[PDB]
Image (cartoon, rainbow, N blue to C red):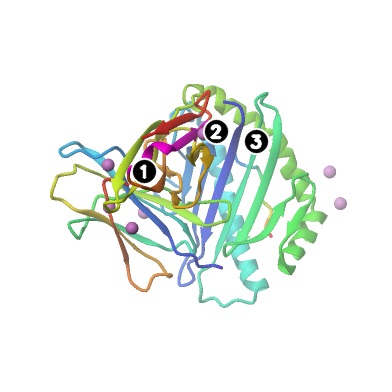
Amino acid sequence: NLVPMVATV
Amino acid sequence: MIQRTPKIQVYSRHPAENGKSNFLNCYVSGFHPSDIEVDLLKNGERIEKVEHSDLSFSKDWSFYLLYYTEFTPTEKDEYACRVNHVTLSQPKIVKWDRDM
Amino acid sequence: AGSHSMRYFFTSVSRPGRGEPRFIAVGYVDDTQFVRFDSDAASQRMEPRAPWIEQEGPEYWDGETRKVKAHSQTHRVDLGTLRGCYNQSEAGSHTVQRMYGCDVGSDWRFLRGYHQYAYDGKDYIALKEDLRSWTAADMCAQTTKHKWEAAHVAEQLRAYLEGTCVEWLRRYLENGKETLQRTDAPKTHMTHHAVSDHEATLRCWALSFYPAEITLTWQRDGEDQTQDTELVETRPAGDGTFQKWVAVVVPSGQEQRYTCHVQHEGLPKPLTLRW
Ligand SMILES: [Co+2]
Ligand SMILES: [Co+2]
Ligand SMILES: [Co+2]
Ligand SMILES: [Co+2]
Ligand SMILES: [Co+2]
Ligand SMILES: [Co+2]
Ligand SMILES: [Co+2]
């Protein structure tokens, strides 16, 4: 189950 | 760096016997950058029906792939893996040695 | 088995002449791939790669597809941002790589979590062991760290690693128990190949094993020997299991003083092989 959000660098 | 040359192992899935269907593997690992060309050869000719795994990588970030095809070994037929990558001035051909 | 992990691996590779980066995602429980996404493939969906994940219903697949596409877009944006920070041209291809996941112990409780990110194969930014702050490798990553500190990015990620990640790992271990919680001990044997008339290679083989972690050790008179040895990288068989060998060159006639030990989770006691 993937992480729900992925912040941009 | 961004560039490290692939390690190459060429092997059958099972211990090879003549006339018995098997899988020929070329495992390439430890490489960067990711762009790579791998062909499996039968008596020097590129084999057409070749599959590969999804690109993944190790702890040090270097990449690995498995290329594979079903084959039925015979006494006379010779097999190999041909790899090209930015670290290699020409393609590298590694022969299948059925003891390795 | 009991220590277990769930890990995801993501690679994006830019295509500077035209269009968007190539994006590949793969998910594992221990050493078993269970899902994949490839931007070049036709489905444009997260796809199953193990039978036990096919249990999951449409809401699961919709959600994982949505998230994996969101991962892909963050990678796309990052490739642009990083090209700018390093003052690189539009000419060259560049890569981002991300790996994250969680480990549970035998009691199936949280043991540790992790999230690492690289640009062009070099460390960029990673979560520290405490899951509270970031390790930035260079000054571009330091700018990212300040941004992420202000936006409380670690706190969100930590919630997942200690929460959803370990909860769904336990779910998958239960659903796939028949394979995921089964150890496949190595099938071992030794071969012997003359190098000349007066020396020979002994090769200790371990085949068809799971999980991938293994130790092969050569001994002479019961003490470890590393000189004149060769150990290959553990390699996939292609059927879900793994292979490895270790070799030693010995004087011919002296094979009997050498022993190979094989250690693996599937063996109650290490094996000892002797020619
Ligand atoms: Co392909
Ligand atoms: Co604050
Ligand atoms: Co808060
Ligand atoms: Co012999
Ligand atoms: Co020889
Ligand atoms: Co000599
Ligand atoms: Co011993």
Asked whether the residues under marks 2 and 3 belong to the same chain, the reply is: yes
Q: What residue does disc 2 label? A: C60
Magenta run includes residue C257: yes
Secondary structure beneath label 1: strand
Please tell me the numbered disc located at residue C103. 3
Q: Please tell me how crowded label 3 is: few (under 14), some (14-19), or many (20+) other residues with Cα within 10 Å.
A: many
Front position among marks 2 and 1 = 1
On the rendered structure, is C141 left or right of B52? Answer: right
| Dot 3 amino acid type | Asp
Q: Chain of mark 2?
A: C
Secondary structure beneath label 3: strand
Mark 2 and mark 3 lie on one chain; the one further toward the N terminus is 2
Whole-angstrom CA distance, mark 2 to mark 1, is: 50 Å
Q: Are marks 3 and 1 in contact (CB under 8 Å)?
A: no
Q: What residue does disc 1 label? A: C202
Asked whether the residues under marks 3 and 1 belong to the same chain, the reply is: yes
Mark 2 and mark 1 lie on one chain; the one further toward the N terminus is 2
Locate residue C98, reporting x and y percent: 60, 53
| Dot 2 amino acid type | Tyr
Looking at the rendering, in which quadrant would you find the C terminus of chain C?
Answer: top left
Magenta segment: C253-264
Q: Are marks 2 and 3 in contact (CB under 8 Å)?
A: no
Q: Chain of mark 1?
A: C
Q: Is the residue at mark 1 in contact range of ligand 4, meaning its CB lies under 8 Å from it? A: no
Asked whether B80 or C90 is in front, the reply is: B80
Front position among marks 3 and 1 = 1
Image: C184 above or below B25 = above
Asked whether C28 or C71 is in front, the reply is: C28
Say which residue appears at 70% left-offset and 38% top-offset.
C112
